[PDB]
Image: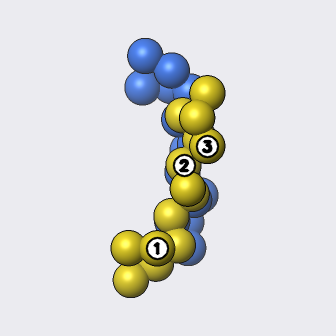
Chain colours: A yellow, B blue
Amino acid sequence: ASVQIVYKAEFXYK
Amino acid sequence: ASVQIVYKAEFXYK
């Protein structure tokens, strides 16, 4: 598992 | 389409 951060505007482990 | 930036560690319009 790892931290995932997304910027798409919208901005959020698996 | 829009700008997409991902942090997952690695760090990249679709």
Along the line of sight, the residue nearer the viewer: A10 or B8: A10
Number of marks in the image? 3
Chain identifier of the residue bearing label 3 in the image: A
Say which mark, if any, is on residue A13: 1
Towards the viewer: B3 or A12: A12
| Residue named by callout 3 | A11
Q: Secondary structure at mark 2?
A: strand
Could you tell me how far apart the alpha carbons at marks 1 and 3 are, in whole angstroms? 14 Å
**For the residue labelled by badge 1, is the local secondary structure a helix, a strand or a loop?**
strand
Marks 2 and 3, how far apart in space?
6 Å
Residue B6 location (% of width, % of height): 54, 51
Q: Amino acid at mark 3?
A: Phe
Q: Residue at x 55, y 56 (%)?
A: A12
User: Which x, y percent locates residue B14?
Assistant: 42, 26
The disc, 2 or 1, on the residue closer to the chain's N-terminal end is 2
Reply above or below: A4 against B1: below
The residue carrying mark 2 is: A6
A11 or B11: nearer the eye? A11
If you read the primary sequence from the N terminus, does the residue marked by circle 2 or circle 3 appear first?
Answer: 2
Specify few, some or many for label 1: CA neighbours under 10 Å numbering under 14, 14-19, or 20 or more. Answer: few
Q: Are marks 2 and 3 in contact (CB under 8 Å)?
A: yes
